[PDB]
Image (tube, coloured by chain):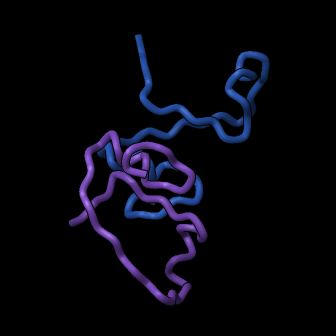
Chain colours: A purple, B blue
Amino acid sequence: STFFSTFKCYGVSATKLNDLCFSNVYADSFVVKGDDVRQIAPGQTGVIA
Amino acid sequence: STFFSTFKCYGVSATKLNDLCFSNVYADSFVVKGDDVRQIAPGQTGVIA
């Protein structure tokens, strides 16, 4: 059903998420416009960041 | 005539293609939707990969 236009993982490889166990898991949610999505990453400047 | 929205070379630099000779060349063709193009790359996960 659900498909994503952006997927990025930083401290782990994407092909090893099935063999791991995760601790202290949190999820954040909000809405922005298309041109502002690139700002959601470490070491970024701009209005959102 | 032809223009590409995506182009990414991996084991060679893009400015060296005109000076080399290539062996065992093969081409693969298929169709996906726009959101799935990002999965055509080494180390990716998803339904396509």
Counting the numbered discs, the total is 0
- Compared with residue A11, is residue A39 higher up or lower down, i.e. above or below? above
- Compared with residue B35, is residue A12 higher up or lower down, i.e. above or below? below
- Compared with residue B31, is residue A25 higher up or lower down, i.e. above or below? below
**Farthest front residue in view:** A47
Residue found 42% across the figure and 46% down from its top: A38
Q: Position of residue A49 (x, y in %)?
A: 43, 52
Q: Position of residue A13 (x, y in %)?
A: 59, 68
Locate residue B24 relative to residue B44 in the image: left or right. Answer: right
Q: Position of residue A1 (x, y in %)?
A: 21, 66
Front residue (pair B47, A37):
A37
Front residue (pair B11, A46):
A46
Snapshot quadrant of residue B18: top right
Check the picture and name the quadrant holding the N terminus of chain B. Answer: top left
Residue found 74% across the figure and 28% down from its top: B22
**Farthest right residue in view:** B20
Locate residue A33 relative to residue B22 in the image: left or right. Answer: left
Locate residue B25 relative to residue A49 in the image: left or right. Answer: right
Residue found 51% across the figure and 77% down from its top: A17
Residue found 42% across the figure and 16% down from its top: B2
**Farthest left residue in view:** A1
